[PDB]
Picture 1 (tube, helix red, strand yellow):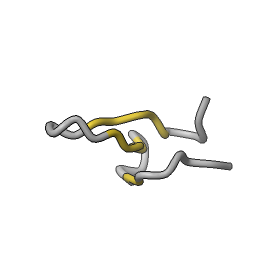
Picture 2 (spheres, rainbow, N blue to C red):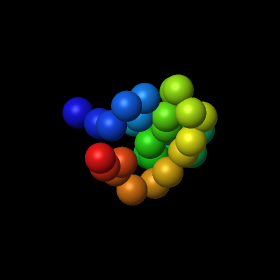
Picture 3 (cartoon, rainbow, N blue to C red):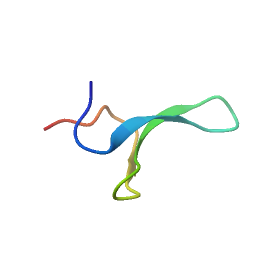
Length: 33
């Protein structure tokens, strides 16, 4: 699936990104490890 704590997320305008629930980090390209 994804690295530790990362999951898919989405803006109110319909734009998709990735979010870490453990570390509160956020990024647009798919996380890797």
